[PDB]
Image (cartoon, rainbow, N blue to C red; front, side, top):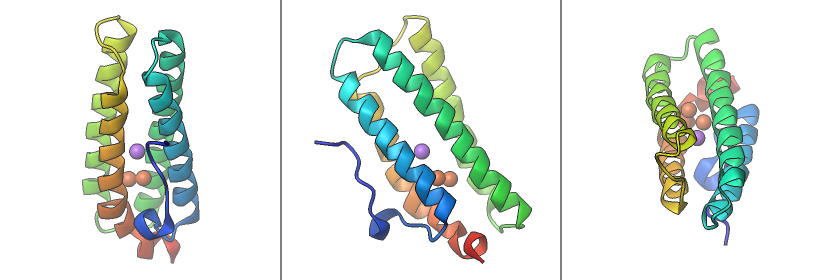
Length: 131
Ligand SMILES: [Fe+3]
Ligand SMILES: [Fe+3]
Ligand code: NA
């Protein structure tokens, strides 16, 4: 049972690149979720690291477009990104020190974050970025 399922109704932004990057995030989170129910710590870490790298790139992609187009709520939206990047960096620090584990609570938090962020934050840039 996949943790996350993308639909257009719930998550579509009317912005092609963003919808595509979102669908990749959901697939990479789903993979990490399944791995996080095991004790395969090396595989957990590789999938965690891949997912974080991709998310940071997604945020940059959204920010570069918002800023270039003079989107009204760019700085607020970047602030929400930058707080999750700080949480991700802190988790990588603790995980790669052997001080914290990644488990299905970790991936449920990323789920919770995304399923709030996409509809309530990302969908707001649609009109600007699809114009
Ligand atoms: Fe997004
Ligand atoms: Fe965003
Ligand atoms: Na995300």
